[PDB]
Image (cartoon, coloured by chain):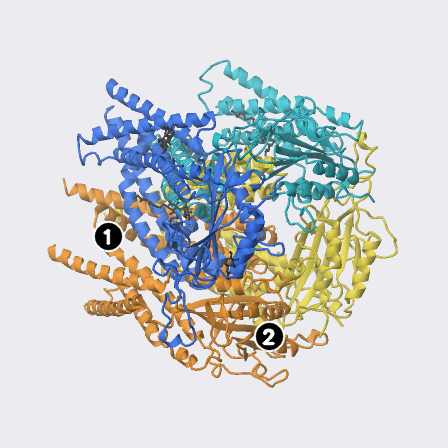
Chain colours: A yellow, B cyan, C blue, D orange
Amino acid sequence: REKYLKSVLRELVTYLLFLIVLCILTYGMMSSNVYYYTRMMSQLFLDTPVSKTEKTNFKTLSSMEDFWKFTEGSLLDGLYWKMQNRSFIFYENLLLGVPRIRQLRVRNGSCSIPQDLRDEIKECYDVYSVSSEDRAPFGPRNGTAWIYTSEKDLNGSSHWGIIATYSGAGYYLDLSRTREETAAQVASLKKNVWLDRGTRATFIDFSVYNANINLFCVVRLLVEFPATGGVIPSWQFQPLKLIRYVTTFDFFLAACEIIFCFFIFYYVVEEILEIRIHKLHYFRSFWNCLDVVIVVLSVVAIGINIYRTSNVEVLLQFLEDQNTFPNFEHLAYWQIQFNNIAAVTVFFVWIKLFKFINFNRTMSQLSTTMSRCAKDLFGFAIMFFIIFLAYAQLAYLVFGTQVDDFSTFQECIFTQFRIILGDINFAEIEEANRVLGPIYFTTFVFFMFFILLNMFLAIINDTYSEVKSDLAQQKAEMEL
Amino acid sequence: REKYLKSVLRELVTYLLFLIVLCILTYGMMSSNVYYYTRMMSQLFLDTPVSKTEKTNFKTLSSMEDFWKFTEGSLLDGLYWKMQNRSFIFYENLLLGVPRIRQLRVRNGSCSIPQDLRDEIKECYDVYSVSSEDRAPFGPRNGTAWIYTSEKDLNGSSHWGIIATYSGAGYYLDLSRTREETAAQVASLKKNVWLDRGTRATFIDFSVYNANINLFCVVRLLVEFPATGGVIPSWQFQPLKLIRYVTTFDFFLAACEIIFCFFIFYYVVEEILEIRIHKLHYFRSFWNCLDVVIVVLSVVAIGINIYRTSNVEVLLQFLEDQNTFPNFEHLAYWQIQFNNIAAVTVFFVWIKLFKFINFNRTMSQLSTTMSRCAKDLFGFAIMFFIIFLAYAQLAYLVFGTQVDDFSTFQECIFTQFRIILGDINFAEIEEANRVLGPIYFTTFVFFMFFILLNMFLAIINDTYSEVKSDLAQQKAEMEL
Amino acid sequence: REKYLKSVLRELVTYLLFLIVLCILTYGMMSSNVYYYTRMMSQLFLDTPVSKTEKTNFKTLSSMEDFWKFTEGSLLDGLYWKMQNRSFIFYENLLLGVPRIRQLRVRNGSCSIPQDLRDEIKECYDVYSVSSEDRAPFGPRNGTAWIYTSEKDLNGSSHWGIIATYSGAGYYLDLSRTREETAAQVASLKKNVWLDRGTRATFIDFSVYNANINLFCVVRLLVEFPATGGVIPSWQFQPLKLIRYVTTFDFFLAACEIIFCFFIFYYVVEEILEIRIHKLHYFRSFWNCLDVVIVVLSVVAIGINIYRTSNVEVLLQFLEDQNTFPNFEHLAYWQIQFNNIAAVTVFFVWIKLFKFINFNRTMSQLSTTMSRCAKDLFGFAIMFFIIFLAYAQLAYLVFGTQVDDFSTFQECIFTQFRIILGDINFAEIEEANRVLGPIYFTTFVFFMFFILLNMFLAIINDTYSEVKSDLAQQKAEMEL
Amino acid sequence: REKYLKSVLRELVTYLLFLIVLCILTYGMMSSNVYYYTRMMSQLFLDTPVSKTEKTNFKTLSSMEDFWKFTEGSLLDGLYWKMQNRSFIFYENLLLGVPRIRQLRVRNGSCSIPQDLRDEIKECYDVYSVSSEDRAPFGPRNGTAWIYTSEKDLNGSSHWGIIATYSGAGYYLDLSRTREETAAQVASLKKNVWLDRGTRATFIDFSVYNANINLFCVVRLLVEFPATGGVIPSWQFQPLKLIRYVTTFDFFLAACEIIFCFFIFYYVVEEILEIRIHKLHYFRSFWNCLDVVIVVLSVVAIGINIYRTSNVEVLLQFLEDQNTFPNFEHLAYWQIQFNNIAAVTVFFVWIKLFKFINFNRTMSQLSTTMSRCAKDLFGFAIMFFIIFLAYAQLAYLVFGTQVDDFSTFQECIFTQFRIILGDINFAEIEEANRVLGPIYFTTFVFFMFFILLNMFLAIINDTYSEVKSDLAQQKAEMEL
Ligand SMILES: CCCCCCCCCCCO[C@@H]1O[C@H](CO)[C@@H](O[C@H]2O[C@H](CO)[C@@H](O)[C@H](O)[C@H]2O)[C@H](O)[C@H]1O
Ligand SMILES: CCCCCCCCCCCO[C@@H]1O[C@H](CO)[C@@H](O[C@H]2O[C@H](CO)[C@@H](O)[C@H](O)[C@H]2O)[C@H](O)[C@H]1O
Ligand SMILES: CCCCCCCCCCCO[C@@H]1O[C@H](CO)[C@@H](O[C@H]2O[C@H](CO)[C@@H](O)[C@H](O)[C@H]2O)[C@H](O)[C@H]1O
Ligand SMILES: *[C@@H]1O[C@H](CO)[C@@H](O)[C@H](O)[C@H]1NC(C)=O
Ligand SMILES: [Ca+2]
């Protein structure tokens, strides 16, 4: 018992040191106010009205001419700021290099006009795919904006947008350091008709740097031009910390990174020495599976932070020439992947803390309750999600062309979780379909929220009463 | 046991093939992005401001003169697009033929002015009914806009609107291919006063075609003119796929339609051979009743898809002359009916999957729980809906003239489901009636959400504890 | 048993006839679309912008000069409509007579300036009470707008507003039939400064009549001028049916009124013959108490419908002279009281239906469950409302000066019911107080929604398990 | 038993007198309509558009030039009102003295530009701290607006803002009694560039007095200028009652204050005489701990109301000279502290009422239920908050740079309480991260709302069934 308590004590203090080091590392991932660095950029570029007589945003673009009014107007008035040269956005954020506008095109004849309509309609342009993509030169043909450049040649990568996944290739134009040259270039693209019926996407990419808080911010504005016509705007404001060793707390964060990877080396050694004793008996446990998940996610985090996130070859390459476009699209991608991995790792490391709070009879009753009802809650989770996805496919077939919240199948699932909580927009459901809007909503509230929601609760009630009346009979019958 | 498992296995693989074929069919009913084809049309016609100095939408029309500003303004600037002839909306969507504006009128003297007020008020115009409807010529009397045309003669059908159900007859005017002729026609209707005090509805109907994604879109804009005065706008943007065999996946969808109707022939043969053995004993089951519901809904789906939805006689009739109005009002109606039928059929086919997940002792406990509490949940559902409709009739008598959410009795029911979830607009309830708004809301939250909502939960708790303690005593007493 | 079933059968068919007659009566109280008669009047007078260069509504008035812009602007453009004389609003609704603007004033010196500030501040005007009210003539003193008229002399009655209850007396001005005379009168009130620092309320009253649907609509617009400065607007659009016998369905409604008061005579005779047998034993029942409540509310409904609602002496008095103000302020008051009484009566008549659904063993189990848990749910309702009003008084002391939803104590109670459901505006709570906003919200969610909400549920679970295990032991032990 | 009931009776009537006196005291803390005194000031200064061609508020300031448009525009049009001298805001609220604008600055060179960027970027200005704060004179150097004044010399105190805690020192400028002198001063600050890149905060402070209701109102407008660039506006409208003895009800409130502090003297004597008998046995009770909490909070309330809130030395000092700035920043601070203390004291005094409702067998069952489940609910509250803060740290790492509701860690906690209720903005979560937005939301709804929320409920169900079946066996076995 003293050796069991000694081993529990040393693994507890090991885990507590590990949890302290990890919570220090994610204290330095989040600087104190980066939200007020992304929302000023967002409200400068997305929320300002496009022209002085227009009320459209970037968020509410609806046409191609609104996109030209944005590119000639709010984009140029946001990027270029007159000095008290080169532009400091909000007189703080240095615009790095030049921005870049890039277009993706589909071919004429990339779809098939039906045989009874080949007299009336001459041309058709398919939805964006890589097979449908246009490689031909067009327009005046005398620049990089008019000639196709491959994905390998403009150092790009695939972007996952709202209606398609867009290749990193296309028809790009790097802009200029000053507003007047850039306005001349945008007017020369609009005059020669650069965006037409074959256009399926337009990317606007630039990067700023804040010397005060030492953060880059990689901006990507995407406008998707569907085959149906119109405009779907999308944006991405992504901060990067690419220059690490500036302040003392950054050196302490580097020290905690080293101490963290020593902890992860220790846990990988420990779980390998535990799994070698017994093979499939190791996975007949929840905590060994959770330790496997933690060390896999942590090795993936160390791998991203070595081979991807800390490869600032493009930054030193940009610091040679300030008149080019800085390719920060890969650093931002792997910073997003690293933040997702690290957040999920911190989550499961806090879930691991439940090995060490069976310190009491009450906590042991709670733990025994949920471990004994896990199987029956999983069975009813299967049954619940069968009825839940039946309703989601019903709602997708009924409202999928009319309602924003039901437009894709996963959005139907997430909308139903919101309906179960109470986040409804029933006005648009009830005006999309006036008979099955009502019937869908009322039968989903009755059969899910009144009845099947209470069945998880019934499983937990019965298991808690069983565990209490069993561990009380065990406590009494030993005392008799 | 081996033959029972063999029959269960063959009906399981039959059902799984059927579910795969049906989920393929409703993968091809929903194209990937039709929502972005209806919302661009909606934001072009509903959400654009009516005039350049006006802020009213079509959604926020409040008067007859706002309707004339819409018909002279946002409607003409949305329909007619200058080519790089005939108009391509968003340079993608071909306007098919001409649009059509149609009016429904009631008679002077169609109601009775009370005897003490026949001196002051000369004329009264009743709420729209078919008996009150005006058949007389009026105005200049020299067109189709000024002379009544029956429902049989303009090929129309009854429309179910917000305050009435409107006959397909009336005073119609087909518009023109170009903007200037159509503006002349609308100005000639406004000059001669076409809409006056007898007007009860105005329909605007047109159809576009997108060659890129191969979808028609049947637009119907309704403005209802109540007897109280004012305007109630209503719209309907409905996509159709009327040209089937264009792509290869469409041929695969046709093959899956044939394989589906062979499955439905198989299930109708099976359920007839099962019902012939025993009459009313067949309906003493849930799964035989569900199989009856599935084959009835599926036969109705096949009947709509043969005798109604796949009758594109008006499309080939329209392709002869591009200067007429294409009657797509029936195809859109039966496409809505087919989508409702098919969505409900897919829902119950997924519910049928619960015959085949009694594969475990836990799943059998869950199934036995809900099948044994079904009767007592139905009894308390009767009692709950009696108190629920008592509150709904209370709230209709109190707020039915003041609040949008309580304006009709079914909307009172749906508003109370939203209050139970937590979708409240209590500001308008509390300013409609400051005493019974409060009392209604607080007693509805106390008696429904705190007390009667927990009674379903009590039934499910007690039935689950009973089923577990019974199937555990059955498992133990057989082992003793 | 046959005589018991015979008496139950005759009282059941008596109650069913009574419920049919009552549901017919409240089918004719609610005409089919009165909501679209109040919202057109509301959107004409409340929601139109006050001036063509102004964006304020009547709903968003914030100053006295905005009130003059409304009275010179949106009010006159809403009331007076040029004919194709006298004004038909939306060319349907006849403006009856002239409108009337009325002011309530407080005295100079109606409060006490503190002794250290009687040098700087000369005058102070107390919050509106009847003791503080000004009776003096003022201004040019040569009209009814400048001379006090008592409540008995302008036939008015007390109005219960947002911050005070306002007497029906004051300084009134009846306006005119045409727009130009009324604009001259409003400009003459603004020139001579009619609203100043003593003003505490301004009422605007008018009535319209719709000949098409046979409804009056009594409009009262109130602007309250607090002692703090500013404007609190308030409105009331109230439809009346003052001319009864016009259509055939109205005669059938009168016949159902007579049959209803015969039913209420029958039930009063029955409950008096039942209460005379046994005194306080009669009130030891729920259904006898509910019958007492129904016949009291029904006698109050008949009394309002005879002595108040059907006294259309002011209507025939108005029909003599169309150039005066029609006093419909009492008819609207008693129509609101009659609608409240009748809605509550219909509610309890539907609750009475539970005497007659103990037709089954399951329904008897549900009824026995709730009748046996009524006492313990009432005890925990006492305990719950003690903690609930403790939180409401906490939230009133903390947010009562900052948040709209916590401004009065009853609004704190209703806001907490909304928080329990999930209708939160946490942004304004969290910016009103950044420490106790959080602590109030999180401890109210934890202690009410997680814990004390589940205690009602515990009472109902235990009582249902007790009633089922008791009525099953009664069913088994009789069979053994 | 008679002496036990006698002691319970005398402590009950003592507590009831105490509760009446305390509820009278917090009836006079809240005047009837102070909310309509703060919202008129708020809608005058925050919600009016900044210029006649601008639509920005004070609430929606986004730049430094919008702040100059506010200070030259809406602030001057709100403060200065032309008389029928000195300004009465809404012709009721006397502007006391002059306002004051004050700036906080950071030094050039207060951060470290990284070594590879010291060529491009010359200067950097750190986030506001006291060590980074600028003390140097700047600009024209010939006023108080251009020369640093310490916190001890301008009588200020530290302000806790949104992104920092701001010292009470800085660069202040007292404004003027009239609009033209103040406009000259603000134009002279804008001309000489008073706000530049070193500015981190700008305070605008003024005080009004309403003679009608006898309330001061201390306004503090804060604009925070982050290092990222932009503007974060913040406000504080705080009413004070600094002149006590004006009306008779104020004398009754003073009498109730004296009677309250006599009650608190009585309870401190009683709890000291009870704690002296037994030391740590005293704290083995809930009601003795609650009495300790009440008398500690009440002594803190009396201490604030004597040594801080009732020290109106600055008011009589201001009444000598009406041309200076009245320092009401300390009185408002301690009035906020006193309102927090008094509201929490009233809350726990109402919670103390549960000593005296064990008057019944049912109330004793409810009390015994919650006192016996307190320990197991505390254990599961520990386990629940471990999983809850694991999710909050996940959501802070994922959405903390993108979403308003997740910007700080405590706001992540409060957002998750809102998600559990049903106050979601899922659109911004789902567009911040399209993979972990969904996964976070759905796994938080499944694991918290479906499963772990029902575990508190299971504890309460089992404890209530145990207490009922135990106190029924105690009632029966004594009767056998
Ligand atoms: C017992 C089995 C149940 C009985 C059978 C069910 C009832 C069958 C007939 C119901 C009519 O079917 C109903 O038709 C109306 C139009 O008339 C359709 O409505 C559709 O068009 C109307 C207007 O035309 C729109 O207002 C509505 O938003 C749209 O959904 C509705 O979607 C469909 O659901
Ligand atoms: C014990 C049985 C309960 C005691 C009897 C109940 C109290 C009877 C008297 C209550 C007064 O009845 C109450 O009158 C006010 C106006 O004064 C009505 O209010 C009505 O007009 C006022 C203004 O005039 C509006 O503010 C309010 O929105 C409207 O509902 C309210 O709807 C009605 O509910
Ligand atoms: C909870 C629901 C309650 C709804 C029912 C309320 C009670 C309504 C019935 C009360 C008696 O209803 C009463 O009907 C008589 C009919 O002779 C009406 O009388 C009116 O018309 C009759 C005949 O047309 C005239 O002789 C009489 O002078 C006139 O006042 C009276 O205006 C109405 O007051
Ligand atoms: C007196 O009444 C007349 C109307 O007869 C009005 O025009 C005039 O303004 C009033 N006198 C003053 C001083 O306002
Ligand atoms: Ca909710």
Query: What residue occupies the far left of the structure in this picture?
Result: D2
Residue D183 — which label? 2
The reply to whether residue A353 is visible in this rendering is no
- Residue B407 location (% of width, % of height): 49, 38
Query: What residue occupies the far bottom of the structure in this picture?
Result: D142
- Sequence-earlier tag: 2 or 1: 2
Question: Residue B132: which quarter of the image?
Answer: top right
Q: Residue at x 48, y 67 (%)?
A: D91
Tell me the SS state at disc 1: loop
Can you say whether B458 is above or below D378 in the image?
above
Residue D50 — which label? none
- Work out whether disc 2 and disc 1 sit on a shared chain: yes
Answer few, some or many: residues within 10 Å of disc 2's Cα (few below 14, many 20 plus, some between 14 and 19).
some
D471 and B84: which one is in front? B84
Q: Label 2: chain?
A: D
A389 and A125: which one is in front? A125
Give the residue at mark 1.
D357
- Residue A415 location (% of width, % of height): 55, 44
Can you say whether B177 is above or below C219 in the image?
above
Tell me the SS state at disc 2: helix
Q: Label 1: chain?
A: D
Q: Amino acid at mark 2?
A: Ala
Q: CA distance from mark 2 to mark 1?
A: 64 Å
Q: Taking the image as four quarters, which one is ligand 1 found in?
A: top right
Tell me: is circle 2 under 8 Å from ligand 4. Answer: no
The reply to whether residue B90 is visible in this rendering is yes
Mark 2 or 1, which is nearer the eye? 2
Can you say whether B345 is above or below D172 in the image?
above
Q: Amino acid at mark 1?
A: Ile
